[PDB]
Image (tube, coloured by chain):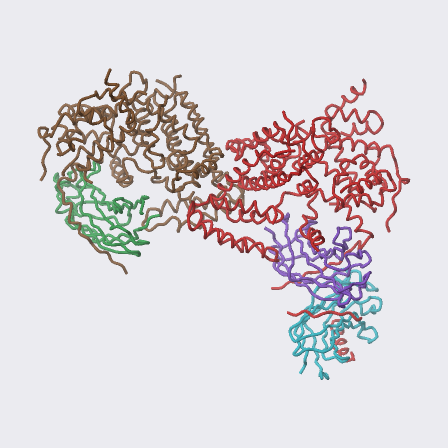
Chain colours: A purple, B cyan, C green, D brown, E red
Amino acid sequence: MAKVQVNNVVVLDNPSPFYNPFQFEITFECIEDLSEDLEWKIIYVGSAESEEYDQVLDSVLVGPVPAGRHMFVFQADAPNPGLIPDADAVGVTVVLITCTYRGQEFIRVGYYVNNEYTETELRENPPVKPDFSKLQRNILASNPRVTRFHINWE
Amino acid sequence: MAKVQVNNVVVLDNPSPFYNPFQFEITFECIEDLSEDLEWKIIYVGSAESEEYDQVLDSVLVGPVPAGRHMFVFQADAPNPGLIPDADAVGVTVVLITCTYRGQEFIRVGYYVNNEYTETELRENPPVKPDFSKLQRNILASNPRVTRFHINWE
Amino acid sequence: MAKVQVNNVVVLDNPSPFYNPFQFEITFECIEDLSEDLEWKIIYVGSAESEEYDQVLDSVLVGPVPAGRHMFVFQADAPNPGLIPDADAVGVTVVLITCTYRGQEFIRVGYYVNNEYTETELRENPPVKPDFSKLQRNILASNPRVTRFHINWE
Amino acid sequence: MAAVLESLLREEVSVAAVVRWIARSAGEAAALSSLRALRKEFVPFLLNFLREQSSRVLPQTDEPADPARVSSRQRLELVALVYSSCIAENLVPNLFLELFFVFQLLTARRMLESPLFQSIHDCVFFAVQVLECHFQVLSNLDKGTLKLLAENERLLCFSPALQGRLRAAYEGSVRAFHTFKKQRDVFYEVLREWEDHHEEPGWDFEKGLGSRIRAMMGQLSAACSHSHFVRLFQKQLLQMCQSKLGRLWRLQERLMAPQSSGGPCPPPTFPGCQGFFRDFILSASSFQFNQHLMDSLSLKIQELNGLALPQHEGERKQFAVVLLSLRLLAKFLGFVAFLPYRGPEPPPTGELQDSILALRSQVPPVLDVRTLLQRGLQARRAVLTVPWLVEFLSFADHVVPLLEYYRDIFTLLLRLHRSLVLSQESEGKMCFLNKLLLLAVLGWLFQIPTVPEDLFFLEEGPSPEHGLDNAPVVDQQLLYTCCPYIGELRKLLASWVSGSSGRSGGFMRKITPTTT
Amino acid sequence: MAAVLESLLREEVSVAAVVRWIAAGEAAALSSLRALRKEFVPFLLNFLREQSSRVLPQGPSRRINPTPVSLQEEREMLRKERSKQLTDEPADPARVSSRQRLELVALVYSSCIAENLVPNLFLELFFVFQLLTARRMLESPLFQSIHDCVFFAVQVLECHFQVLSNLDKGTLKLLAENERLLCFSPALQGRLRAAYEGSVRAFHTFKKQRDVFYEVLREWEDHHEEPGWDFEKGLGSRIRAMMGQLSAACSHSHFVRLFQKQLLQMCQSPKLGRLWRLQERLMAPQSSGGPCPPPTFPGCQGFFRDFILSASSFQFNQHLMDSLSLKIQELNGLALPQHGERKQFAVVLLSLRLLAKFLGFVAFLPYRGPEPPPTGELQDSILALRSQVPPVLDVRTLLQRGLQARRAVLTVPWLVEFLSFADHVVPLLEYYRDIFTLLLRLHRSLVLSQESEGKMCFLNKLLLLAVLGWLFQIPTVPEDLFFLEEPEHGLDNAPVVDQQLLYTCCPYIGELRKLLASWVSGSSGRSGGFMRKITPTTTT
């Protein structure tokens, strides 16, 4: 029986242009006090082909947690457009948010990312190479995929 | 009557060290739709001896606002320690949040910020030069100050 | 599970002389309506050496039994002194109460009975011929005895 | 219906000839062989015919019996001889159930070529005639039955020799954690509460103890210390369930009598103190607890069956204790093990049956009974092992007889039954009491509705040391304790004279109850 | 323990001699260390992992969009209040500290790996790939630099072509594209390049019970992916009531039949080309559980585990336990024809593994305790109390019959997985020891370098070795078992095993690709050092 569970996650700043940093709001419930600091990660899958184009955004630690429920807001920087292959630079992809405790991952949440040209002529026929000044990022918050793992806590 | 009403301002990530960015969760009101962008700024007071030490941290622009109870999270960077006077770096100072519409402001909000050393041996006899590497920032969110104006809304 | 449960049995007119008739008030509850009429029986134990000295005082057949709790009063005649041997005439005896459904006993109720002379001299020096005209019978209502069995009610 | 009965009644063949023909495997044999198709059907046809005839007589101004008023003599004598010779060669499964039927015939009161038993005198004469051939079995009953049977006047009227013989026979007479302690304290508290309040009217076990027990089990499962709890449970059950001042106990024994109308062959039921644990186990509903209990009980049963009892020829009392403990443990193990499959529906014949047999036959049984029975029987010691084995099978469901594994055990038991001769002592080299106990316990097994009734009839044919067999270890007290239904013959005898004077009977006097 | 290592280091004996000894003066010299033969392999392994610990890891005009659901006046008050308060280095061969000792150690390691003395092959390969994947910071300690580590890893990895040529496209692509191996062995990288371009009667109430059961499942698969969902809290009431009704109606057989049929039907299997590959990322296993993850129920198999854990009735478990045993017994003896293309083998194997998993999980549930028996004198009592009850399935006889008539590939997988969910005391019993020693004997004989002995396909040997190497690292099984313990042509010959089946049987194999992708994703020293800390906000 897991102790810490997420109760609601709400995405902020959507839709928005490509260069805006990511915003999230996470609340979670706790049964009994935790001994060590928590850890969170955000992973952006640059290319749908394989995992060689993964860009890590940021990783933070959460202070000591007493019993009860808490809320906080997570912020991370924009991804580097230079490392993304030009084939995957338009279409759909996946953004991963994961949590680790005592060096063990125990819950993963992911979203579908919609990257499309705002100008309809570029959406009907896009340019030969990207223009990141005209792209817009959309996150499908209506269908969040989650998966939880059983780990050791004591 | 004021078309835009500030309901509540919530202070996040407190207490925190100096370099932690400002995180204010604010909910505002709109009686009717607004046809132009709302500009928000965060102003840090530098010194009580003179007004030349005040700094501007960040500003944001808010998209079209229909009538409702919309909310967004304001994020601002930490003040630069290079311009704050030494006699004012150690002590307690004020931060200000204002709103502007069409180049004229209608509300001013001010919070009180305490820059207090954490460790007691440094608290008793602080050194001559303020040490931002270990100092702490505390925000007294329980006692805010409010001021309201009449503005040419039409 | 048993469809019929006996709630409480209350002793009437205690003590009383030997010739006084036996009296009982029977409280029982039935969960569902039965298909046959219930029958009751009482047996007096003349002696502990053999079952040949039992008297069948009376037997009654209750009318149709719907669901719910039911109460009724039992009336029966006194035992005949002639059939009782003198050795067990004065001492301790037991009276039994049994109820049968489909001719199957499922609850047996027992009560201790102590017969003793009222007069002091008769108590100290009883005569050779046990005089039943001066004997008082008492019922120890403090210690009822009940025993149940598993039967095929359907 | 068979043609043999009227043929023998009309003086064709000897009774001994038909008894040898039925028991084994010049023109008399050829005449008998012409009716070979009815050989198997003779015994139940005769038993049903005799039962149906008594319906006129049996209770479904008094006239004393008279030996000179019989309707006929020859037919009754032949029928009685046939009946006696059927018991003498063991053609019937349960001798004491047949003794109850003749005793019932002995106390008739009121109301083929020709129907028999047209008068009370004929029935009484029949009952007297058949009883005369079984002096040996009656002579080893209890003292009270000898009292009652030696004073009746019917035997004196019809046979003074029998009365004299019975009268003369009278003179023969005698690591764990901390929470386990809290759980055991709660368990002892619950035991004390039941010991005190279980007798008062209105008590319901489930409503009064259906909450604390489940919580105790849940916390025990969380702590994972079932072994100690099971050991304590078994020790407590074994210690407690087994066991002028001569008047109080005798009188109180009336108030703990078994069901009156259930005799002579009643279904099994836990009496007295043993009934407490049944509801505990039923309301526990725990998977781990049941598994640990089965393991512990199986190990305990197997360990005790191999005791090497010393013998001498002083006295020894350990035999009764070990036998009773084995019986109790086997009964509880059998009750627990076959709990899931106790379904109230027999399996209809057809292709659908084979699927059930295939599905239920690939799992081994919880205790290897067959090898234990085979190994024990080879080295005498049958009296020590048969009773608890009989108790174990008594709780099985309907499928078990249809299975292949247990048919060998049933065939072995049937082969053993036919060897249990009572008269033929010169070759048995066995004591009478052991024979009487084994015959009574085997004869009770075939009466349960679960076992098919026809298994006893439809069988073509069933076919060395100094051990515990020869010693007269069984006592009359032990025989009566392990065979509680034997004493109902005395209860029937007692009712003969009790309901004589106060014969009211009718006028049922209906009474209507009241309700709020 | 280190005497043999010192002797081999200072050129006293030959590697082949000690290899043959473990598996005329040289024999006499080696016989002087007779008592230390059994401890050589674990000591060498531990010494290797210890020396690796020096290098391997320890263990303003912004715009927003809304989301629907003079400064002189303040100076006086502020004054009053204040008064009141008052770069990565390249690798090349030339900076190596030594060559002879490193070459000897690498050769010994490779010889030990090739002859199958180590417990697990893939664990050692993952350790070689870790030693190949580091970048920063006896007579004498080893590994003063990254060069030394890279040279050692490349020397060992040179002699294992055959295993490296049988994985999927991705790992071969990244291994042939590697930027470091070009400095140490161009021939090996050309070889793996050519390989890459070379690879291509019932009651009426049963209807109500079935309808309720179908309604229950329609609640799970459409709401088990929303955050905050709980199984027992949301469904712990209806299931118990339905199961009690079933027990009252004494109709467990039909419900068990339906349950087994549904479990077998659903749990197998219910631009598209890009969507299918993209979806694989979200369903990935634990990112830190490898290379020996504990048994788990991924995918749709987890629903039944929680269902059983929630029901907890006596009657249901017995019926399920019997039915699964019957289905397993029936399916083992199917006579699969051998000769076009055959596919039924995959279905049979995937069914058998799942059935064995579920039976093993149900059967051992009561005994799965937390602790071993601490002593050797009290333990025999529990051993005696436990060993008497016969097992639910005659597994030893089934294995013995299977191996006697070839059929090796069709029996070992599901049998090996069945023992996975055992409790902690099983290995101490008398019965299962024979099964374990038979498995040891089977594992020893399989050698990848010999093919003339018999006729077994290479992929079959690889699958058998990989499966057998995962059982012995389960925490329940004690580690000392490995070291202290010391005809017809048929199914085992035909090439029935494909790459897809091998990768589906052992998902942990693919973690080698993850370690290669981690190297190239880390194209610079991004955001190293101290990291931001945030204090949580609490509400009441």
Point out the residue furthest to the front here. Answer: E340
Picture coordinates of residue E257, whole percent (x, y): 50, 44
Residue B116 in sight here: no
Query: Does D89 appear above or below E496?
Result: above
Tally of numbered discs: 0
Residue D462 placement, left or right of E431? left
Q: Quadrant of residue B121?
A: bottom right
The structure residue drawn at horizontal position 73% and vertical position 55%, both measured from the top left corner, is: A43
Q: Is residue D339 left or right of residue A96?
A: left
> Among all residues in the image, which is located at the extreme right?
E94
In the displayed structure, would residue D47 be above or below residue B7? above
Residue A78 figure quarter: bottom right
How far across and how far down the image is residue D429, in percent? 32, 17
The x, y position of residue D154, in whole percent, is 13, 30
- Residue B97 in picture, x, y percent from top left: 74, 73
- Residue at (72% x, 78% y) in the render: B35
Q: In front here: E64 or D410?
A: D410
Give the residue at x 13% y 25%: D160
